[PDB]
Length: 197
Image (cartoon, rainbow, N blue to C red):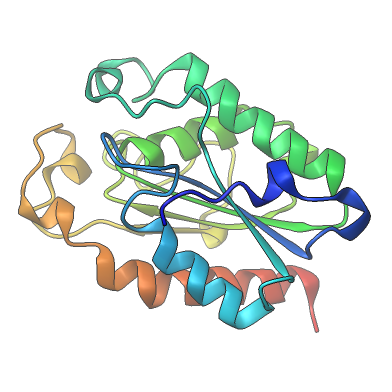
């Protein structure tokens, strides 16, 4: 339902071409929350169920409300978890194109993980989508150390976490349509641009 561990469970003798690592919002269930499943069915339609591995960030990422107040908008243990998944993806499947995403605290987690990531693996991440990005104002709409053209931020008007606050208002809960339409289309386009055709 909201849990996919395709990378952890995948056999490196039969790597997928595309690996998607996604971090859920604060309090959400499984390791994909509300938005992850929608992005995953679209990517599966585009690449085939065997062409893409969907991996939510689980393990030490508890997606606690309190961790939003920590320096980079999430915990050091959660950043280590997501870094470990990018490292695992590169180790099992060095030829796979990576794509990433996150919602709310998961968007701050994706941004911090990519900032800290070895640049050689970071270059393999074709695109990242961020929804309700809690460090949008602070980071001026960017992921540190990652190019603007591979980044797509979805921040609604009235979503206060995009404007430097941590108050959750109704526009923060309105990213469902983006996750099923423009966000997977962006990711698919960026995969095709690095892979070519």
